[PDB]
Image: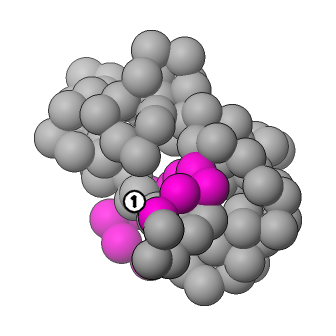
Amino acid sequence: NNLETYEWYNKSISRDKAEKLLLDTGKEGAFMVRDSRTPGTYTVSVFTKAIISENPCIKHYHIKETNDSPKRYYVAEKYVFDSIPLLIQYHQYNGGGLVTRLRYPVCG
């Protein structure tokens, strides 16, 4: 599979960098992702210039995995998928109850 091709995905990336990269980009609901050692899912950096006490805003949403059919990945026991792209596509298009659902995938 691999998503090292999504405007939002960030492999070698970390939790801090994405925010830095997302913060620099400057987008409302900027979305990024970063692979993790977890069950085999990726992380999702969702940032939206906001917070009068700490902005812009960069949230890291991890893609939960659940041996479904085919569903597996999800971030909020909401929608699981067989790929972050779809899982992201669901947050990119539809709109997952997040900082603003993949409003705009970022790529540091």
Q: Is residue 38 magenta?
A: yes
Vertically, is 3 above or below 22?
A: above
The x, y position of residue 83, in whole percent, is 50, 35
Q: Which residue is mark 1?
A: 62
| Residue 69 occupies quadrant | top left
Rendered residue at 72%/67% (across/down): 23
34 sits to left or right of 39: right
93 left or right of 71 in image: right
Q: Residue 31, can we see it? A: no
Disc tally is: 1
Q: Main secondary structure of the magenta part?
A: loop
State how the image is colored.
one colour
Q: Residue at x 69, y 37 (%)?
A: 104
Task: Residue type at mark 1: give it.
Answer: His
Region of the chain picked out in magenta, as a range: 37-51
Q: Nearer the viewer, residue 22 or 74?
A: 22
Visible residue check, residue 90: yes
Image quarter in which the N terminus is found = top right
Q: Which is nearer the eye, 49 or 103? A: 49
Residue lying at 64% horizontally and 42% vertically, measured from the top left = 28
- Name above or below for residue 1 compared with residue 82: below
Taking depth in this image into account, of 36 and 29 the one nearest to the observer is 29
Q: Position of residue 79 (x, y in %)?
A: 27, 28
Classify 10 Å Cα crowding around label 1: few (below 14), some (14-19), many (20 and above): many
**Location of residue 62 in the rendering, given as x and y in whole percent from the top left corner:** 40, 59
Q: Quadrant of the C terminus?
A: bottom right
Q: Secondary structure at mark 1?
A: strand
- Residue 2 on the magenta span: no
